[PDB]
Length: 297
Ligand SMILES: Cc1cc(C#Cc2ccc(CN3CCOCC3)cc2)ccc1C(=O)NC[C@H]1C[C@@H](NC(=O)[C@@H]2C[C@H](F)CN2)CN1C(=O)C1CC1
Ligand SMILES: [Zn+2]
Image (cartoon, rainbow, N blue to C red):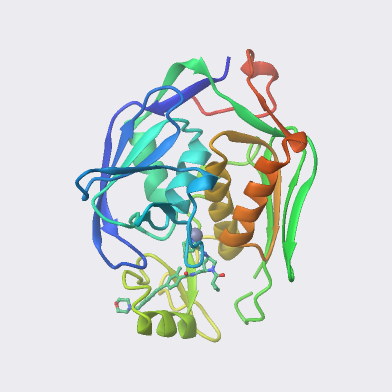
């Protein structure tokens, strides 16, 4: 059967919050069967734990935030993206501050740290949300859709009226294309005028060319350029994969975004969860006949 997984070993990492500019210590801990992903603010007494679930999403403007009372965890989507892509079911994520560290702007450092520690298969069936009906949400020119699909896949389109925008569409079937190789290294990005404005509103305090593609009116200012010709849309897919993991189970289906972001992705999640006719929970007694597959642990 397809079994739940956690970490084989605890993983420690250090970085800065994109928005806060704060130094943060991250610890990823193994977790029991059916824990899910749970963020832990260990700088607080008592410790505040927020399950990484749709119902615990806050503001959503700058990034994906988990909230419980007046406590938040900012910018969860790249780490959730990394765990989603390695099929981690159960893990405690401990943080010494309000924000997940941005690392290089991509999921790559998180996927490396996780795969170094290795995965542990657990004696319990992995549960899948299978998309049964199309579920779409729109607002203005943005749209986000679930479509039934015997596998897992993400299609995304963006349309910046900007000299840098290279391919603005991409589609990845993750049963036949490597999340690790093709998506995980895709870095977040910021336009210079936006960055200047957010800096002035005491936002983007951790930002640098070390953790973001910085774009002026014409070009990438990052000296060493891009990791993929289509890095911007690839990063949009990475963000979506992170947000999709707030469903609390792995997806069998296809996601399609058209200029979508954290707010519309969240509306899609709530709309899916609410329309119980559109999805079922499945398990797989036989991996060999399953529509999705996983790397050896
Ligand atoms: C990445 C970033 C970086 C900086 C920054 C910065 C910065 C600040 C200062 C410097 C220069 N300094 C650094 C210190 O040394 C001196 C020079 C460089 C960069 C400031 C803002 C952002 C930003 O929010 N970009 C949003 C981008 C990325 C994407 N979304 C994501 O990826 C989601 C959200 C979050 F982003 C992580 N997941 C969708 N998207 C957009 O559609 C934008 C057009 C709206
Ligand atoms: Zn991102």
